[PDB]
Length: 92
DNA sequence: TGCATCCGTGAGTCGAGGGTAATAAGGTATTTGCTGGTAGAAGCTCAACGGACAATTTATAATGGCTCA
Image 1 (tube, rainbow, N blue to C red):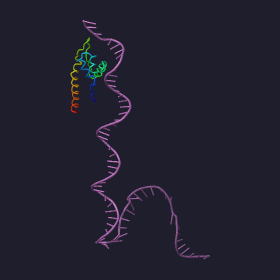
Image 2 (cartoon, rainbow, N blue to C red; image 1 turned 90 degrees about the vertical axis):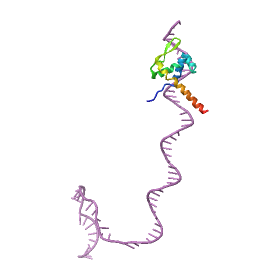
Image 3 (tube, helix red, strand yellow; image 1 turned 180 degrees about the vertical axis):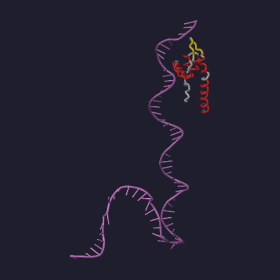
């Protein structure tokens, strides 16, 4: 069974969506456009089947459907960036 | 002109078992000839690496809606 992992892009914008509280401001930190955020939520939804946020006026709140899947994203990028540091540091 | 004398001929499809034997010497030395064995060519063959192209992703461009005070 081929292990269909989540896309390499939807995960990082998902962490900055909660911190920045705004989707437009979530794109300036990742030097991308705001339209790229909505492109990747659907592809990752194929595995989840749960909606990631609940709409609020001029605000972004947390829903339990996507909340379970927040807790298994923020540690992936932490260690891989650490991983980049280790080879780079030992190379020097 | 008569005499032995020699030389081919004398059917054919079919079946079954189907092949045997009187006998003969030992040396020497030299020479030839093959046969596996073991090393060289040589001849692949699987396993890693370098250099163009296209199905698939992504992000970039708008576009048109869903929301409170």
